[PDB]
Image 1 (cartoon, each protein chain N blue to C red):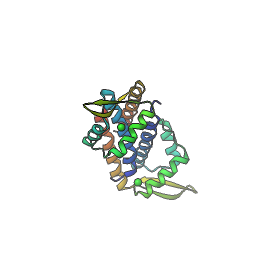
Image 2: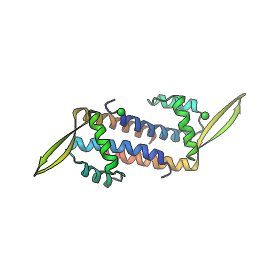
Image 3: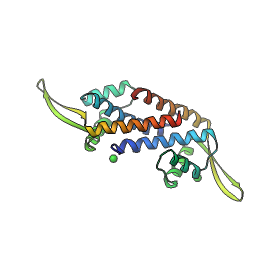
Length: 102
Length: 102
Ligand SMILES: [Cl-]
Ligand SMILES: [Cl-]
């Protein structure tokens, strides 16, 4: 990367936005998010992703539920009403920058 | 803002992108960048801007020159060839995120 500082900041923002995008659409597990973000070309690990999930919930933008399904306890995340509003604002900001410089 | 953490990260990235965009197009003084970024709705001060200019130059993406014009010494910044290449990569990253989530 010619500009690793841009890429680092932008990637943090991108990851956050992708998480909200996916969690608004359906319930998601962290394990699946790691794979889906990776598919899209974002370098993430459970070690980096789970703390961002937890922070998103602390921010009120996700809510999680522990479920026991098929004998295994797992945590699923979904967007809250505040998270859907955030998703709209975050996307708007992205759309504006894209319109301005491209 | 519903998501201040997204807005903080995204704005740092946006400002960096704008700086390269302006410095590729012309030579710039810091004082003018402050005004131009402010016009566009970015909250920037000399305290935030000058350190990012310095880091951009350290990264080889900008070069600055102290220049005496009309009897007054000022520092001007412009993009280097590496900075122009970075601008292209940063734009590509923006384009990709726009495709993914919009
Ligand atoms: Cl760096
Ligand atoms: Cl978890």
